[PDB]
Length: 45
Length: 87
Image 1 (cartoon, rainbow over the protein chains, first blue to last red):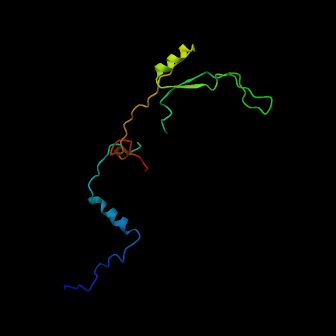
Image 2 (cartoon, one colour):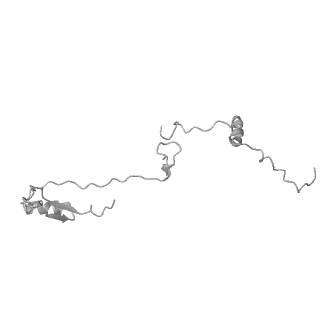
Image 3 (tube, chains in turn orange, yellow):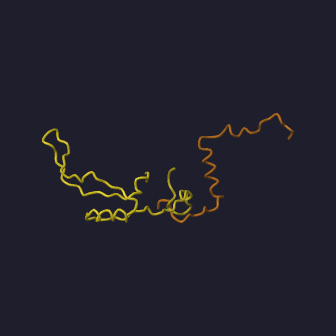
């Protein structure tokens, strides 16, 4: 528990994957509240 | 897109026969009043020069491009279908 200023504990980025960013984004979806609706389904519709 | 040629009334005569020469074949003609184009600054002056010289005339009123409201912010509209897909 020291003032271990000689260690770079941010090593979690080493063991990441190709799909990591989109993976935990999907897991994070349930927390997100419903998005606003602009009415139409598309700017062209 | 320039407009500096739509500011003066023009007077012109109806076209006539234009055949081809038996020689090399230019566009011959027999109507002297074929290239005569006159310019007038106002319709009233133009329509007055016709019958004063004794010419049957027809007059077409000036077409003024109607003012159109244009807004750049409409290009990115939250609801309206005027939002563009490219820029």
